[PDB]
Amino acid sequence: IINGYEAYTGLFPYQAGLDITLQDQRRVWCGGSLIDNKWILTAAHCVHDAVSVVVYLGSAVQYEGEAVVNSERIISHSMFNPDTYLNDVALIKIPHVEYTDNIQPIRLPSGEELNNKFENIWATVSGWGQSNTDTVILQYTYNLVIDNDRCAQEYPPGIIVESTICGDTSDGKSPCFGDSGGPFVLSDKNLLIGVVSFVSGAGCESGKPVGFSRVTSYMDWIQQNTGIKF
Amino acid sequence: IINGYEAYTGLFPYQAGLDITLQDQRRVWCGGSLIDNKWILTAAHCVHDAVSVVVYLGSAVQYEGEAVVNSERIISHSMFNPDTYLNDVALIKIPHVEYTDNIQPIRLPSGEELNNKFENIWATVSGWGQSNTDTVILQYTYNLVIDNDRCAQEYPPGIIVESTICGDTSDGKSPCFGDSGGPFVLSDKNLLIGVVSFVSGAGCESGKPVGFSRVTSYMDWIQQNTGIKF
Amino acid sequence: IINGYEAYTGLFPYQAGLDITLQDQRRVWCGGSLIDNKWILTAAHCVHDAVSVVVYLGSAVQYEGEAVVNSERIISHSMFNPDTYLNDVALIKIPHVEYTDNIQPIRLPSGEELNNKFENIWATVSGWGQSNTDTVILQYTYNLVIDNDRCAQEYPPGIIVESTICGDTSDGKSPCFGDSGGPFVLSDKNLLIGVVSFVSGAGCESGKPVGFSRVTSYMDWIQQNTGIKF
Amino acid sequence: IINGYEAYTGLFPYQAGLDITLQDQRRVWCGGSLIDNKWILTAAHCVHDAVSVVVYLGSAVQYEGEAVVNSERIISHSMFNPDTYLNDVALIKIPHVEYTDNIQPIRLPSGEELNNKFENIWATVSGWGQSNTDTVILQYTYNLVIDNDRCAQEYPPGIIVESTICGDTSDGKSPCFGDSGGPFVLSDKNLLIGVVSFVSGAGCESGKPVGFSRVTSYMDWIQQNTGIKF
């Protein structure tokens, strides 16, 4: 997160830290959201070629956690398109983790929330991605959700689709590399509305909107693959 | 590095820490070696699909450095084979950095050294890869160089080639994920003999040898691409 | 607030901005908390000698508000002691303001919360007081609540009493001049636990605890003077 | 300033903005005049109980300056009477500031000017006091200097004395709360004749005269305390 603020342990109890080992032996970092005792929701671009994932929960300090578990299964969206970031969502199954004061799930949309586009709403994004600073502490910032029409003109045709939700970064506060898969949340409602998916080709300090996977568009996929009815 | 020793600033002044941003926006970590004021030698598997790299020099703390520089250009071996790790070498051109107590280049082999296979010599490998400990301090260990024949027996046929140099990890001391691109050095000679290339399919704690790109095999390529004679 | 972060309009809907004119004609700024449609809770040191107060509500921008009203009456605690800051609480009666999306009351303690000391809890403090920066935007930070025994040793004898609640500023984030009267809140419970009362004689960047009026100790006074049963 | 004109940087290069921290920890704003590279002349009612002051010079924007300096010492008139505003003058010693296009000293009266009462001359008053507009830009207006006799008739007996100089505000243009300590200057002569001292009990919009400390009456005190001869 560029120009973010430091979180303390317990502030974002649903935040997951993912230490990912790829098929090519590289080590990648991504964020994720705890949506159930046994499930983490993240971005497909983070784990589509992952071999294993160490999941950190319950701490603002990177590579630390009140619970540190290994992924049991990775379910990357089958129609994920690497070129357009279309369908950039994935589920990581983990051993049952008991909720505590620092480990709590984030709520997923249901009912009417499924038809809400959340335009012009301030949401909170958090992660351990690149920042102007040198810190291992979880950072966060607020981004205003903009309408898809305005967002679509900031990217090449075809990138911004119905299943995309964008956050404005015109104030210089923005998710950056390493924040991928992280939660975009309506704090008031403890509701997950997006998953950090992509930053503009212009970079994190371009003032361009950041793209997120619109959670309401993937609720069927989530329920079907987790078997959980949210 | 699993079961390694803890380094400190100034101990390995040729060690580069690479914070890599990939074309797919993922953030990757790799090590490298300072071979000239403007050049870093690392593994092709680390940066073949990278768009930019932040280079940390002169500090044993991960993501810290006496000199923090951005890559100006990345030259990855055009004949690199992702499947076999053949020709796993790359160069990162950086803006001229002045050598200090904590920032020094490592010697590259020349003349007769170019014909040495370095069999049965203890070499030092260093990096910030997985260590089974949550530390941000650079680790290192000594691995014995074994002959390619003995090493080939431990890998699928065709993986270990003349341009591969292996380090034995039977002591249980071994480079691991995240150490990729790191230096394999003959300490007493201050000579670079290998670049961390691949771990065994069995993992880091299997006592299997680790493969490195044999530097003597790429000295022509390095000189061709850097325009520097050694 | 020193080393705080910027709030957006609607983030802290209970925050009040007070533009105070004193008996000596000086113009002072203090924060306050909206506790009812007709009442603002602030510090006695801010208004004990005030002639009039302009109350700003509903905006993160200083001197701006969705509702801007004038005080009708000021009720400063009769036993306020200027020398020790004992009983540093005051009520400002204002014309009925209707709650909106950006103007909401903060909840006051009741029942069991009245016996809770809130030790080792992270609370949020906000205001437009002195900051390292040049900004008219409301800032906030988090301070850990410490026990009174630890706090008492950081000040001359007699300053820290039962009715005082302290926040730790050892991380360099702290309320500063102009933040006086502002809210110290348990965000999770939307609960007001303290009113910014005093900074150490050593200043805002001393790392010394900041004293707040412990709201639970003044609930009777509040209910009796507002006539409202919380 | 009520009903004044908007200034801009460089227009009143002698204007000082004072962010004052009081002994009671309250934050107060007052204006002042740069009379020397190391001295600011202001009102005693502003700083008699102050512990420190941040001095803003060279900018028309409140809390901004080409030079932002901290007070080194504050000398308030020892015979200042809070009840009558008698001897309402103070000096703030600051670290030597170099004059620029936007930072220049104002002339102080000497010789014959010391005997001039300046009756019936238009003087310019400036400040960031209350303006019935939410602006952060310095305002100014012209007020006619009236004779003390005419002025005394508008105030309770004994308030207007020989060391008081009054400005008529019958046009509805008047200094107001927050303008305290500001300069009252004969523009064409670049001469300081008064320091904003007090507004009428009737308020700023009553057309009553505003009292200023008559600078010619304090020239001896200023020289005594600054060790500078004018």
Image (cartoon, coloured by chain):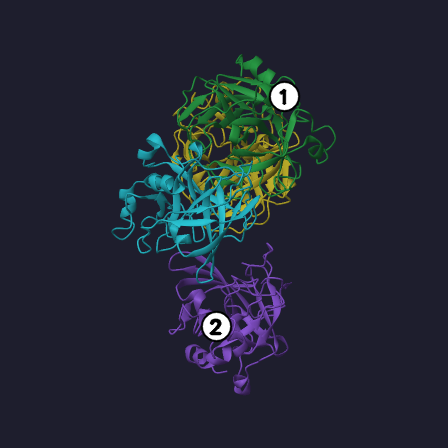
Chain colours: A cyan, B purple, C green, D yellow
Q: Where is residue A119 in the image (x, y as percent from the top left)?
A: 33, 37
For mark 2, name the chain: B
Q: Give the image quarter of residue B190.
A: bottom right
Q: In which quarter of the view is residue D51 placed?
A: top right
Residue D138 marker: none
Image location of residue D97, percent across then percent down = 55, 49
Report whether residue D83 is seen. Answer: no
Q: In this view, does D227 lie above or below A111?
A: below
Tell me if residue C114 can be seen: yes
Q: Tell if the residue under mark 1 belongs to the same chain as the one under mark 2.
A: no
Q: Position of residue B137 (x, y in %)?
A: 60, 59
How far from the left and from the top, in percent, is residue A221?
Answer: 34, 42
- Crowd tier of the residue under label 1, counting other residues whose Cα lies within 10 Å: few below 14, some 14–19, many 20 or above: some
The label nearer to you, 1 versus 2, is 2
Chain letter for mark 1 = C
Q: Quadrant of the C terminus of chain D?
A: top right
Nearer to the camera, B156 or B167: B156
Q: Is residue C212 left or right of residue D168?
A: right
Report the quarter where the N terminus of chain D lies: top left
Three-letter amino acid code at the position of disc 2: Trp
Viewer-proximal residue, C189 or C16? Answer: C189
Seen at 64% across and 40% down, the residue is D225
Q: What residue type is labelled 1?
A: Ser
The reply to whether the C-beta atoms of the residues labelled 1 and 2 are less than 8 Å apart is: no
A84 vs B25, left or right, is: left
Tell me the residue that label 2 is attached to: B39
SS state under label 2? strand
> Which residue matches tag 1?
C217
Marks 1 and 2, how far apart in space?
A: 66 Å
In the image shown, does D126 or D214 lie closer to the viewer? D126
Q: Is residue C14 above or below residue D32?
A: above
**Residue B170 position (above or below residue C83):** below
